[PDB]
Structures are given as structure tokens and as C-alpha cells.
Image (spheres, coloured by chain):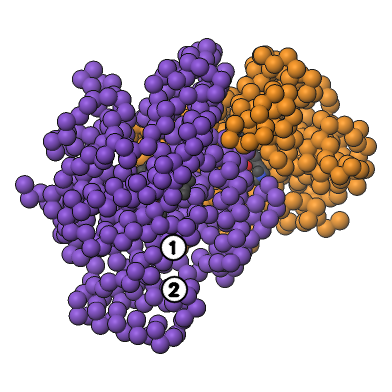
Chain colours: A orange, B purple
Amino acid sequence: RFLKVKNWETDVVLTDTLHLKSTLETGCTEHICMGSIMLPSQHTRTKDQLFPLAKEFLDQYYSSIKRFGSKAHMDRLEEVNKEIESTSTYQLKDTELIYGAKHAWRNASRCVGRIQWSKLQVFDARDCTTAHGMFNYICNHVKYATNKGNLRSAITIFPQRTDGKHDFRVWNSQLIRYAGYKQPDGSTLGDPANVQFTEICIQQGWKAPRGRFDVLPLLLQANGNDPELFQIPPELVLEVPIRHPKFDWFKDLGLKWYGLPAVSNMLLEIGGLEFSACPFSGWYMGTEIGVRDYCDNSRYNILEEVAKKMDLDMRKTSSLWKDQALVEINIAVLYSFQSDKVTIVDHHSATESFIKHMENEYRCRGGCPADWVWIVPPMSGSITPVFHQEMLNYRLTPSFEYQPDPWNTHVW
Amino acid sequence: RFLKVKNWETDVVLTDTLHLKSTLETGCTEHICMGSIMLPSQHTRVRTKDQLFPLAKEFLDQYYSSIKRFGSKAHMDRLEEVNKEIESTSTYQLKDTELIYGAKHAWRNASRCVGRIQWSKLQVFDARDCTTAHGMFNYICNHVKYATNKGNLRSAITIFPQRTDGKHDFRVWNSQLIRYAGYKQPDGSTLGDPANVQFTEICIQQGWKAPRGRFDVLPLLLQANGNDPELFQIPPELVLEVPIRHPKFDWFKDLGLKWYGLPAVSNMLLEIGGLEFSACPFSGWYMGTEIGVRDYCDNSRYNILEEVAKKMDLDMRKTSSLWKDQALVEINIAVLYSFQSDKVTIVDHHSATESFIKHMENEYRCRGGCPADWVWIVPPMSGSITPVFHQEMLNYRLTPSFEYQPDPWNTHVWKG
Ligand code: HEM
Ligand code: HEM
Ligand SMILES: Cc1cc(N)nc(CCc2cc(F)cc(C#CCN(C)C)c2)c1
Ligand SMILES: Cc1cc(N)nc(CCc2cc(F)cc(C#CCN(C)C)c2)c1
Ligand SMILES: C[C@H](O)[C@H](O)[C@H]1CNc2nc(N)[nH]c(=O)c2N1
Ligand SMILES: C[C@H](O)[C@H](O)[C@H]1CNc2nc(N)[nH]c(=O)c2N1
Ligand SMILES: [Zn+2]
């Protein structure tokens, strides 16, 4: 009940007590571990269930500010109880909303970048009423977060769900992503991961420039209405041309990527309240672009072309030509972002940062929920310290959760 | 109940029903996932007739189902015979056929093993008539010679007598049959394999004269029938080794690296129908990354990334040059090059993971499932350019099984 985790590279042993405060469920049982299931039913999302959730959240909020069991605490519990009995929901104080957003990041067990959790810039967009207003808020976020390459973490929080018919949703999975179109010859142009979304953009009325790296438009749904298209001003989208510090032919590949990773399709849960539109952003770890975006077989899948340009022996997999090109591709991404002075972290620094964060969380908080399947980078896993680090995965709230894609849900 | 797993690279979806036949625990609960804990208590291993009949019956039902004789008179007589042997003697003996079946299926059920496509072609050596440490040495030598096969490696397992009262255990004190010594220097540096320092000290204390080199093959330390272990040197002509060179880098040979060809795990416990075989060394062939990534490049192992990157003239001042990643690829190229050039069986992580995906799909269709530990199956480099990274996996415990056990020097009662 008081669990130990060991680091097998350093023999460091940490004692976790924080999991005992876990609310939500893992999907595992004592008979089967689902540790590698991408999105079990749990990680996706009445008057009765709402007040215990509010009480739990307010109790931890007032404990964090050392006013647990204080006048202010009891009065707020009273007031929220009062408001819930009446309105069947409630509204967060600005201070509680900031707390809940920072702690939803702090509790994101799949996030390696959480050492930064406390410096999040929270943009309260709860007064937004239309898609045009959502657009305005999202442009201001992008510009704030981008900061001429000196990226700053940010979240923008639109009005909470009420009855589920009045949902605010960003239909894009990230604020900035490249279009994907199926080809007449059978292949795919651009990002294959976004073929379905790119079709719905045209189906909703986009005029695609059918290129390879076309920044998708935003598809914004306010108050449960039909969603609307808006183009992000190009001057707000910081992109990096990808070149290599050795291979001069690298630039001829035509590669670029955007500076700002901005997840926009998740659900933020605070004190039982649900924020279905809550785009957040930080900065990339290099492997997200170079390993996953560029070399996944279901993505831009450039390995075969880069390997040819390197004149590697691609006859037999045992020459490790894939691995050799993978490393060079990732050297170039880091090289390019650093050259253009756009914030980026390599997987060695980020994972070392996370070990220090874990140490801090165990020491000051009693634990740190962590999903090893996601924390370990997708290349060079065992030469990063997280590979040898035992982690306990459990679900704390406030949290970011997954939600169904809107087009499946939207009553039109 | 059905359970579906998806491959996120190919959208293939599979349905698991085999998890219903799962007996042991995982360590996880609805409220915590222990999926990255190295040795949960549930994976580690004094057992009465009470709980033993149902373990034997479950195993024998499985066995006779596989041979299409479920409910036959042979099946019922065997159940009756095992029943009476337990109540009369408090344990029972496996037939040869049952032992072979159990050992193959313990491999088949090993959810952390990526090499399981080969599970049906295991050579089982019955050493249950062994009585002394000298006998164990002889059986192990024959295992090494057979499995090595001049570089054309063959999977094999040698099964020594099962536990009785836990006071007469057969144990191989080595974690692997062939491993290099590690020596802690007075200045704090380590000569040889840092992973084997403690075991090397035991061997030295037990009378081993250590050559004190960087690649000294450790002696076997063998315990029969609960007696104190005895030292034996594997005959060097039986230990196939591969000098490591690089196909393009001529200076790589001058690093002085070599490795042995035969990976042979010797500290695990084989569980079959509730019988516990505490000495069951088994061997296959290497996946390249086991040597080139873990053995050579772990900070806690030979840790040669620094020297290799130095010799490659890489930018080592900023980690974001990915000089560690670059040197790691070159080393793994060299391991695979060296083994193939010497015609010693090896498999690269691309081939092995691709084969495992095929094995896994086949197991879903013909068996209803394939328990798999993603944390262990995904290779320690280049994870997502292998197909297992994108593959959802269900981890559960089936028997027969291989289990961890405590290191014998922590539990042994010394006679002297
Ligand atoms: C500041 C630098 C940041 C870095 C380097 C970083 C890094 C990462 C990485 C590599 C992943 C793995 C996901 C993937 O591979 O697609 C991840 C997941 C995640 N990140 Fe962070 N992130 C950062 C900022 C943030 C912020 C600001 C938030 C929220 C406010 C956040 C919340 C999350 C969540 C919720 C997930 C996983 C979603 C899930 O449960 O599957 N991250 N992050
Ligand atoms: C034939 C070629 C084989 C290959 C390529 C292979 C590969 C591997 C690898 C790479 C691992 C994880 C290695 C690590 O510790 O980093 C593993 C684990 C394992 N292997 Fe296989 N293996 C093979 C044969 C066998 C055989 C013949 C057996 C038993 C009869 C076996 C049983 C196991 C078990 C039980 C584990 C899990 C150990 C644990 O739970 O920690 N393997 N294998
Ligand atoms: C803020 C941020 C920073 C960063 N450096 N990187 C990301 C993108 C990684 C990410 C985060 C997340 F919250 C969800 C998903 C997803 C998905 C779809 N699928 C893989 C499950 C990806 C986001
Ligand atoms: C037969 C075989 C083939 C192969 N290719 N490779 C191995 C070694 C991998 C292995 C197997 C095992 F059963 C246990 C351990 C261990 C350990 C100690 N600790 C890290 C958990 C390692 C064995
Ligand atoms: C903490 C973690 O469970 C531990 O480092 C595991 C990770 N995955 C592994 N996978 C393999 N094949 N071998 C290992 O030793 C490990 N170590
Ligand atoms: C099936 C498996 O869970 C899936 O491929 C996961 C593995 N680990 C991951 N880890 C990260 N960081 N991001 C991912 O998208 C995934 N995908
Ligand atoms: Zn689990």
C-alpha cells in the first residue's frame, strides 16, 4: 500500500504514497495489464455525482494554500454546495481554474515535460460565446505561446460543458497541423494522419491548396453550434525549414515543421466540471517530429528516401540503415530548430529533466504518476535514464482526458 | 468476455479470449498499473498437497487437450495415477511427454520474450536423474555443446530435479551459463562486466582463481540436492566467442571487444502443473541489441559509448548532437556484422519484432491470444521504427511459466 519504485541504473529507490489518493481507474486488473492500450474506455470521457467531485477538488485546493479547515475553506465549500443544489453545476474562481489547469498537467502520467507544470500561462476564455471569438482567443494563444520562437507554455479554457448539447469544441487535434490528401495514383500527399480531417474541412468548405505542408484551417464549434472555418494568420505560424549540419542534400528533401505543438482535442476535468475545448501548448521534444512525424510508416515515412540519399545498404535490415537514417533525421530537426532559435528539447535532456522532476515529486508530493510506455522516447530508449526507471501509473484528478471526435458526436 | 487489441500502424484488430484461462496475478489493480515494475512479487517464486491437485489437474487437462485426448481413458487414468501419487507421496512425477510439453509452453507463455515464434522447436534435455554438482556440470556442458552447434545455434533447455521440501533444491548460481567476470577496483572503477561483480566475488571466495581480465568467462557454481555449490570451469573449447569489428571502421577491432555467442539463462524457475524446477537453464540465440545496446552501452555495463564516440570524432559537448545515438547505432552494426561474418546465429531487432508480430497474430487465430509485455518486447533502440511499438498488447500470466526466484546466496543454508 506504500509502494517502492527502483531505478535499475542508479539503485535509487523512491516510496510512493500518492497513488492512495487516486480517484479514476487504470483499465488493468489483477488478471490482465492493459498498460499498452492506447486509449482504454477510462482515458476517454447529474446533480448527485457533482458535489463529491467539487468537495475533493476544493479540499486539495485549500490544502495547497495551507487553508484546509479554515473559514475561507468551509465558506467556499458551502457556497459551491449552495450553487450546485441550485444551478445543478457551478463556476470556478479564477484562482481555482488556474490551480486545476496546472494540476491537470502535473497529473498527466504520459507527459515527459511536466517539470515545467507550474509555469503554465492560463488564458480564461470562459466568456467566449462564438466561433469567431474562439478564433480570436486561439490566435492570441498562438502568438503568446510562440513568442518569436521563445516558446511559453499556455492553455486557453473555453466555457465548460453544461448539458452536452452546448459543447465548445476545437475539431482540430492540434491547432497547427499539415493537411493530408489521398492521391489519384493511390498514395498520400501531406500528412496521412489528417486525411479524414482534411476531407471534413473541404466538406465544410475549405479551399485546399493541395500541397504537402499546408497548414490546416481551424474548425471551431461554439455552444454546440455547427463548426466554422478560420485560417490562422500565416505570420502567427512559426515554421522551421529542416536542414542538416552535414548533408547539404538534406534541404532538397523539402522538409519543414511547425514550432508550436498545441493539443486541442482533449477534455480538461476539474472538480467534476468538464472543459471540452481547452487547447494547450508547450514546445517539442525533437523525437516527436523526427521519429514519429517523419518516420512512422503511417505518417510522412521519409526513411526510405533519406536512406537512399545517404547511399546506405538497404538490401538487408541487419545493416541498420533505418536506424542510421533515423539518427541523422533527428540530428537535423534539433539542428534546424536550434539554428532558427525555436525552443526544442532533445530526448536526452527531457528525460533527464523528468527524472529530476520525479525525484522532486516523490520528495515534495509523495509520488508522480507515470506511464512508462509513453515516457520512454521512441528511439534510443535504453540510453535515456527513464528506461531503467520503474514507474507507477495511476489516475489523479484534475486531468486531461480523451473524448470522441466531434464529427461522430455532433448532431448537425 | 472478448478483449480487442489494435495495431495503430496497420489498423489490424485482434480479439483475445485466452486471457480468460489466466490464473496468476499481474500486480496491477483497477487503481494502479505496475506494468513497468521489473520484478513484481507475482513474477517471483514449500507447497502442500492442498493446492497441488488442482494445479496438476489443470495442467493435465491442458496437456491431454493439446494431444486431442481430453476425457479419454488415458486422460482419466493419468489423473487418477497423479492423484494417488500426490496423496501418497505429497508430490508427483511428470512423464517425459508432459515435461517436454510443459517446457515448450512455459516459453510459449513468456510474455516478455520476443523470440517466441520458435517456441515449438525447443530441445528438452531431461536431467531429472541428476544427483550431484558434477552431474549437473556434465549435463550443462552437453547443453552448451548441443546448443552452440559450431555457431548454428539451437534452442535447448536442461531440466534438473524438481523441488521437494525446498531444502534440497537444485540451483545454478550463475544468472547465465556464460558470462564475463566483473572486478571492483580499489579506485572505484570496474574491470569487466559491472553486472557480475557480486557473483564474481562469490566465485573468488569459493576458490576461483580469477584471471582479472576484461572478458574472463565465469566458472559455473552448481548446487545439487540442497548441498553447498561447487565450482567448475566450462571447457574453453565449448565457449564460442565473437571478436567485435566494424564493417567500415577499422579502429573498432582495436577497442578489444568480444562477446559470447550463446545466451543461456540459468537462474529462473520453471513451473509445470505446480511442480517447481528451480534449475532449468535454457538457451536460444541473441538479438543484436541485447549485446550492442544493453551489454555494451548501459551506463551500468561496459559503457563504451564514450570511447566509440571519441574514436568517431563526434561532437560530444552538447547531447543534442545525438552523439550517443550515433555511436549506439555503429556499435549495433558492428555486433551484427561480427556475428554474421563468423556465421554465429544472431537476429537484428527489425527481423525479430517483425517475426514476433507474425507469431502474435498466429497465436490470436489458433490460440485465442498471445500474452505480451510491451515494456520488454519493444527493443531498447529505434523503438517506433519496429512494428511492435505500434502494437497494443495484453499482458497476463499463463501456466506453465518461467518465474523469477531469489538469488541463492541470499537464501542458502550453508553446510560448510
Ligand atoms: C513544455 C514542454 C512539453 C513537452 C516537452 C511535452 C512532451 C510530451 C510528450 C513527448 C508527450 C508524448 C505524447 C506523444 O508522443 O504524442 C506528451 C504527452 C502529453 N502532454 Fe506533454 N509536453 C509539454 C507540455 C505540455 C503541456 C503544457 C501540457 C498541458 C497543459 C501537456 C500535457 C500532456 C498530455 C495530457 C499528454 C498525454 C495525453 C495522453 O494522456 O495520452 N504537455 N507530452
Ligand atoms: C530463440 C531465440 C530467442 C530470442 C531471440 C529471445 C529474445 C529475448 C529477449 C530479447 C528477451 C528480453 C531480453 C532482456 O532481458 O533484455 C527475452 C526474454 C525472455 N525469454 Fe526469450 N529469446 C529466445 C529464446 C528463448 C528461449 C529458448 C526461452 C525459454 C525456453 C526464452 C524465454 C524467455 C523468458 C522467460 C524471458 C523473460 C524473462 C523475464 O521475465 O524477465 N527465450 N527473450
Ligand atoms: C503540449 C504538447 C507538447 C509537446 N511537446 N507535444 C505535444 C503533442 C503530444 C501529444 C499530447 C497529447 F496530449 C495527446 C497526443 C495525442 C494523440 C493521438 N494519439 C497519439 C493517441 C499527443 C503536446
Ligand atoms: C534464451 C535467451 C535468448 C536471448 N536472446 N536472450 C536471453 C537473455 C534475456 C533474458 C532472459 C531471461 F529469462 C531473464 C533475463 C534477465 C534478467 C535480469 N534482469 C534484467 C531482469 C534476461 C535469453
Ligand atoms: C523499469 C523497466 O521495467 C526496466 O528498465 C525494463 C524495461 N524494459 C526492458 N526490456 C528488456 N527486454 N529488458 C530489460 O531489462 C528491460 N528493463
Ligand atoms: C500500442 C502503443 O501503446 C502505442 O504505439 C503507443 C506506444 N507509446 C507511445 N508513446 C508516445 N509518447 N506516444 C505514442 O503515440 C505512443 N504510442
Ligand atoms: Zn497494468
Q: CA distance from mark 1 to mark 2?
A: 10 Å
Using the image, tell me which numbered label, if any, was put on residue B62: 2
Question: Residue B190 location in percent, x, y?
Answer: 29, 24
| Cβ–Cβ under 8 Å for marks 1 and 2 | yes
Task: Tell me which numbered mark, 1 or 2, is placed earlier along the sequence.
Answer: 2
* B279 with respect to A142 (left or right): left
Which of these two is toward me, A320 or B58? A320
Q: Secondary structure at mark 1?
A: helix
Q: Find disc 1 in the rendering and name its residue.
A: B105
Residue A207, visible in the rendered structure: yes
What residue occupies the far bottom of the structure in this picture? B73
Q: Splitting the image into 4 quarters, where does residue B362 fall?
A: bottom right
Chain for mark 2?
Answer: B
Residue A237 found in image quarter = top right
Q: Is residue B395 above or below residue B299?
A: below
Residue B227 rendering spot, x and y as whole percentages: 13, 53
Structural crowding at the residue carrying mark 2, measured as other residues with C-alpha within 10 Å and reported as few (<14), some (14–19) or many (≥20): some
Count neighbours of disc 1 (C-alpha within 10 A) and say few if under 14, some if 14 to 19, many if 20 or more: many
- SS at badge 2: helix
